[PDB]
Image (cartoon, rainbow, N blue to C red):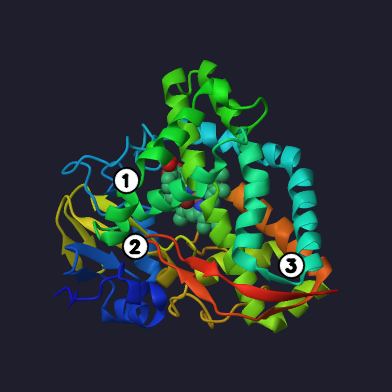
Amino acid sequence: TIPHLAIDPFSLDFFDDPYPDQQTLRDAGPVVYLDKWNVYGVARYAEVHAVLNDPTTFCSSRGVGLSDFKKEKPWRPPSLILEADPPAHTRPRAVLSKVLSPATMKTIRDGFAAAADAKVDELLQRGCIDAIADLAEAYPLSVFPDAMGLKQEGREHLLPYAGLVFNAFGPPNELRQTAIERSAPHQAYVNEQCQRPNLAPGGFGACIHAFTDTGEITPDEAPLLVRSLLSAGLDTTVNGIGAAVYCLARFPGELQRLRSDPTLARNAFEEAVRFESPVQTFFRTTTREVELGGAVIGEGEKVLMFLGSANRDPRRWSDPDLYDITRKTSGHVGFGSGVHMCVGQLVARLEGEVMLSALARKVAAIDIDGPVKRRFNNTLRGLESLPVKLTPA
Ligand code: HEM
Ligand SMILES: O=C(O)c1ccc(CCBr)cc1
Ligand SMILES: [Cl-]
């Protein structure tokens, strides 16, 4: 009753152009079985949203990658928030929610925006820059590690560690095996920076440790929660900002609308998250036999959610393959949905907004003027290199 497909959603060919194979996954049926990896898959918005919003049935404590923590040892100690289910998930979630709260955004917004304007001003001085290394990577590196409270030493480990993390969610292919092979130095650095003495006062890290005397988390839970932000906090915004600039580079008409009304920056970034879905996929594990889109899934089965496919499902979106900065983007699943919905989405949106605001005010045109190179990762979608000429406004 369930169609079986041979598509490998973690193959290089798939990463290079996933959209045809994603329509094939959506249109084969509401629930497919991927013979390559022995997992169920849902690529339509409706089922992706349902799975995300049934955390009891589709749990996260058995891992949100392919590996089932009940069957294999996790490559690193489980995240106390991402790889936990309610109620164990609840209190750590609240702490991270207050650490990255609306009130917290007000303390960092001015510095984040000044750093965004400064970067655009710097890039305009060069003209022909790499929107990835010189913008999508350079900007978050100039604000987030400092907002964390990290020392300068060792920050080169941050992106390699994040790439390792997101590759580790995937199947045991060469991307994952190679990432884990090289992980030791990056794990050592990250784990060490998670300790209270190594986090500058007032930053996200020290604020997490400060919540250890409320009874929401104990002192021994703080390092792993700092680890969460060092895992999910940087490389995501890199690919989110990169996708936004990529969209504006490909859709000059939308850049011109953004210039005409820079208050659209925040929605232009949200639309970029939907349109590219930098975070492409996550797994759940069934805790019982479940009926999902006419299929009966047994207990202990991995289910692969195609977030990016769900964000382009024409059953849900009008003109899904068009970048539209005035689109009503509420409901897209690029930040997830439900109890695990991205707790750092205010940071992500802040960085995205202030950067697109800088571009909206300072840039008249963004033209690709060089080979576009894609970066391959089992979970992240984004570019390795995006040469562009920036024309001053
Ligand atoms: C474009 C930027 C970002 C995107 C697209 C993104 C995407 C996502 C998605 C889809 C989830 C859901 C995971 C799941 O359902 O299993 C998630 C969760 C999470 N995100 Fe983000 N994220 C972004 C930025 C950030 C930032 C900046 C931070 C921290 C500063 C962060 C921290 C987290 C954490 C800790 C979780 C786990 C929350 C939980 O399990 O309750 N993310 N993110
Ligand atoms: O808690 C963590 O370490 C963690 C949380 C979320 C992700 C991916 C969603 Br942006 C990865 C790692
Ligand atoms: Cl680690």
Question: In the rendered image, which residue does mark 2 sit on?
Answer: 305
Residue 373 x/y as whole percent: 50, 74
Foreground of the two, 138 or 357: 138
Foreground of the two, 15 or 21: 15
Q: What SS does tag 3 mark? A: helix
Q: Is residue 199 in view from this perspective?
A: yes
Q: Quadrant of the C terminus?
A: bottom right
Question: In the rendered image, which residue does mark 3 sit on?
Answer: 264
Decide if ligand 1 comes within 8 Å of the CB at mark 1.
Answer: yes
- Image position of 278 (left or right of 10): right
Foreground of the two, 105 or 177: 177
In terms of sequence position, does the residue under pointer 3 or pointer 2 come before the other? 3
Question: In the rendered image, which residue does mark 1 sit on?
Answer: 60
Residue 199 x/y as whole percent: 59, 27
Decide if ligand 1 comes within 8 Å of the CB at mark 2.
Answer: no
Q: CA distance from mark 2 to mark 1?
A: 13 Å
- Image position of 358 (left or right of 210): right
Residue closest to the far top: 213
